[PDB]
Amino acid sequence: QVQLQESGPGLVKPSQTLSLTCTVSGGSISSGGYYWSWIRQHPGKGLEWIGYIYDSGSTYYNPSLKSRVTISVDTSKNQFSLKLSSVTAADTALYYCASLPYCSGRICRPRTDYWGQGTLVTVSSASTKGPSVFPLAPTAALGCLVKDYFPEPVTVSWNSGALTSGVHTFPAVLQSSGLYSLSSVVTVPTYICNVNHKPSNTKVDKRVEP
Amino acid sequence: EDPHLRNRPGKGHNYIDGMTQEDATCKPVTYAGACSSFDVLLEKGKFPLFQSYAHHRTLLEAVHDTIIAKADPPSCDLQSAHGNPCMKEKLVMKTHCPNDYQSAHYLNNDGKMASVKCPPKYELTEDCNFCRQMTGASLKKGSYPLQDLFCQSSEDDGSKLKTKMKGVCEVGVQALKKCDGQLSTAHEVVPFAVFKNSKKVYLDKLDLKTEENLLPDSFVCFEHELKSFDISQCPKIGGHGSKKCTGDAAFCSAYECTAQYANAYCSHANGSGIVQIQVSGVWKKPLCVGYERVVVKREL
Amino acid sequence: LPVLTQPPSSSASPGESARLTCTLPSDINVGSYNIYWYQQKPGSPPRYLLYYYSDSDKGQGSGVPSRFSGSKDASANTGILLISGLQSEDEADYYCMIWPSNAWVFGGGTKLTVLGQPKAAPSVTLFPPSSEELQANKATLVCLISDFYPGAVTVAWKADSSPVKAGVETTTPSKQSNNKYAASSYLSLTPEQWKSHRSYSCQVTHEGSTVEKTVAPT
């Protein structure tokens, strides 16, 4: 029905300003009486509301963050955006945009909750670095090795998404160098893995042959 | 409008600030759902003036459309041992409150909305003058309307209008004149109105007139189990709009009617229109008109 | 601003019922609010389960089984999530939420463990270095460990029969949506160390048992 999609840098330097955008499709942020929100979650920890807009006309913020946070709206593009100033290592988190229901008398608006997938933001003064991709050659096992990138995350699809069954992209290792690696494998009877590291605008397609 | 009483003029917001747990069904009121600040107004028998003008605004609707201002403070701590500024005004009103309400609201002597409020887990007593521990499993989420009234926007200046009642020494909190003699006292149902830059004006008689018109609040629209539809999306004749509409003959005299292709149907709302009231010989356009049962003292 | 306290963890067995609490601070009252509950499984956003105001004012999330229900305890000032007929798929984090005027307030969340789940030995696949990585003067052995329970393993690497400790990088186990765990181990070698040995082995020990996989330059 409604879909939400976060966009943003993945890496910001300490004391700088984090900027993120949420694009809404399937419904209008400008009418209906729905609340459009930013919520963050540091990995392995809780949820913290940041702020929301009601339709596109009023804005309210978490009081402990209000002095660092602005939310703005672009009704023409059906987008809303977040600005978080003076960032610290404590702001590293997964940032979701979301619309959650308010209810009464069995009526909920919206009738179900909508969440984007979240965008990961790492606060660090280290520079971006894109991975090197190597193929993991061969029912049988098959994969792709994505080595030594920063910051997280990397996405791996297979055959531009045509192959999704039997796919497993492993959680990344943090190595002593400070850079990450991961592998994606697919169990199978042409195969290409599509690796994307948005913080470095590195797209690589890797054909992995017998 | 028999089936469209929940299709509200204006925004249709029937909540009171600080009590927002009913917003799904009250902000706005519409065809589906229960709203404790609004449904009591349509119980037949009760609120007969509002039911005669049910396509005009409620007090809470008028407040949220910025027609009526909120009193300061917006709510009176009923239980407070130190008293509260609503107490005098409330005590001269004979009111009946159903159980399970934490709040009740009224148009005060200044023409602003005030409210009496109990602490959480407490309800208003049946005369709405005290708070007691709640009798049920839960409180209602909204506020009980203590007066039978309806409202509308108006720019008609009422700065010169004051209460005139023959042989009345006091009505409500208003001392019309000091009476040296023996007075009688009664709870009487008294009509009143509030105007731009006026206080509450009590009247001996309620005389009203309505001019029907073709303005947006004079229609109700629904998708063509009803779903309401915002008429501002409908193009005017010769104009542009974001959706396609059709409706009755009144609607199509002003809006472009597309019949087959229409997303919605718009009906003229029975009884809507510009209301005026005769006050001491002169017709004026009030912001709100109502009845309330108050102590009246009269010369004997 | 108000703090909603949830116990950090809870646990129960299949078919039992889990009772999760959300305690409001003493200055506000649970009777005043809709209580919303959210479930979060690994790799997904939280999901709305249900809301509860009173026995006559409450609702279930679309697709949320009836065995999740809410209630309130006025004396303890708590909102309660009751999960009856507990199933393995219910292992998750659960957050309570209230919506005072102009704010969303989330509880700290409760980690619910479903007890008695069966032991699952890990699947292990080991990849040798690719010829392209070697051409770039590097060598990485990739040992992938999946779908085990409980989530603890130990990895040891062998060159021929000799243990190798330098150059090993091993993740901590990561819980998946299916309640099982995944891990991986990377052994960095020189191209010439890889070629000069008969074979290398990844051996994963899980609950006393060991799964070895071996690769060789061929």
Image (tube, coloured by chain):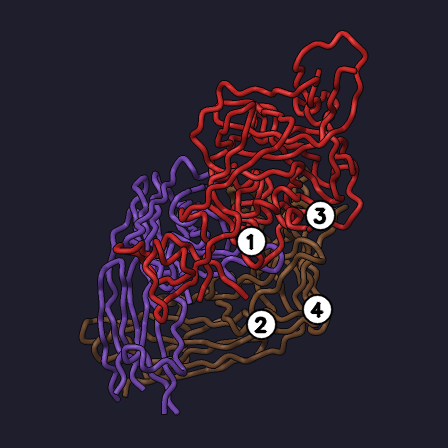
Chain colours: A purple, B red, C brown
Does the CB distance between marks 4 and 3 fall below 8 Å?
no
The residue pinned by badge 1 equals B6
Q: Please name the residue shown 50% across and 38% down the image.
A: B275
Quadrant housing residue B246: bottom left
Please provide percent x and percent y for residue B212: 46, 45
Callout 3 secondary element: loop
Question: Which circle's residue, 2 or 4, is located before the other in the chain?
Answer: 4
Q: Chain for mark 3?
A: B
Q: Is residue A116 above or below residue B294?
A: below
Does the CB distance between marks 1 and 4 fall below 8 Å?
no
Distance between the Cα atoms at labels 1 and 3?
18 Å
Please provide percent x and percent y for residue B250: 41, 55
| Outermost residue toward the top in this view | B180
Does the CB distance between marks 2 and 3 fall below 8 Å?
no
Residue nearest the viewer, comparing B3 with A25: B3
Given the image, on which type of amino acid does mark 2 rest? Pro
Given the image, on which type of amino acid does mark 1 rest? Arg
The residue pinned by badge 2 equals C150
Distance between the Cα atoms at labels 4 and 3?
46 Å
Given the image, on which type of amino acid does mark 4 rest? Ser
Distance between the Cα atoms at labels 2 and 1?
57 Å
Tell me: C86 left or right of C200. Answer: right
Q: Is label 4 on the same chain as label 3?
A: no
Q: Is label 2 on the same chain as label 3?
A: no
Q: Is residue B267 above or below residue B75?
A: below
Does the CB distance between marks 2 and 1 fall below 8 Å?
no
Callout 2 secondary element: loop
The residue pinned by badge 4 equals C84
Front tag of 2 and 3? 3
Distance between the Cα atoms at labels 1 and 4?
39 Å
Q: Is residue A60 above or below residue C202?
A: above
